[PDB]
Length: 370
Ligand SMILES: OC[C@H]1O[C@H](O[C@H]2[C@H](O)[C@@H](O)[C@@H](O)O[C@@H]2CO)[C@H](O)[C@@H](O)[C@@H]1O
Ligand SMILES: [Cl-]
Ligand SMILES: [Cl-]
Ligand SMILES: [Cl-]
Ligand SMILES: [Cl-]
Ligand SMILES: [Zn+2]
Image 1 (cartoon, rainbow, N blue to C red):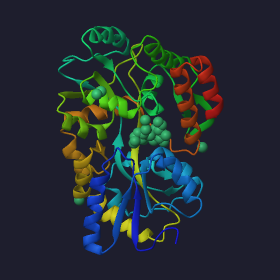
Image 2 (cartoon, helix red, strand yellow):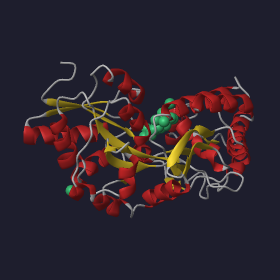
Image 3 (tube, helix red, strand yellow):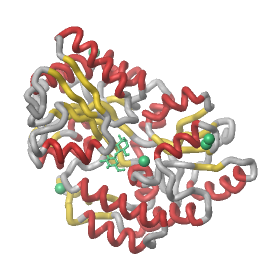
């Protein structure tokens, strides 16, 4: 078989708590005899539609909900069937994220938003504005440090700045997203991307900075700030850097507006193990003990499971996560999101590297997203 009967194969991103998830899998195996194998392929969210379209791939895929409408439209996801009692365990807005064309198509797990993470020893009082960063970098450089480093290769991390002054993905109005109406090339989006490009032009950041570089720099005390999600806190803890997690800086007086993702677990339509996947997700993973196990490996951040979230909310880092989430927007789950992200990734990388002006980059992004 392309997908093996009698076990579960799971995909989750490599920066999440995949070892903790595997532990939940070992508990499952102990109780049921069903082995669970967790993989973390790179770009799994791009690979999934390729392999699932041929009846292959994992039994279960974990990713933010934004990719799931596309998968569902292509018939790659099984309809899930939790009853009302189970539904009541999770916050209503998380279920909204995973409902597509009249069907629930994934189980919500956690609510993710980026925050500003800062080194308290270098910056006891972190900047409230993006505009403060250039001068702060010049001041820190004289002491052998930089102000800020974050992943410039994934547009997820730059979006909060692009959206701050008015950029948006798809217009939502009167109960629908208008997929012909994109906001990646409005004045606000240009302003935010231009600010980023200027940070690079003025040697405050490097265009080639990626996830690993920014994490390395922050966790080694080479830079005073980074922008990242809750999954990153575990490695910072181990580094012994004294850090805080706070509201993202404003731009032109406007809050940064991160795109909020609901990490969700979908079941492959081609899986011969759908009932076992349901048992694993409902009875083992989406439980206090299951999420705690994953969280202990890499923090989930705010979780969809009310009972556990009530405990996590007491953590000031989680409060900061929710504050940033409230200033941002939940991502659409519509199929056009794949095109949107391709468009914006291309624009940010080309603008940052100087291959395109901001105006040309975002003009192309508008065409490509719509
Ligand atoms: O950067 C584009 C990318 O953004 C989001 O992916 C996030 C993901 O949601 C987070 O859980 C975390 O792993 O960071 C990822 C970015 O590297 C979108 O969900 C994704 O579809 C999109 O390609
Ligand atoms: Cl990266
Ligand atoms: Cl080093
Ligand atoms: Cl529970
Ligand atoms: Cl769409
Ligand atoms: Zn280094």
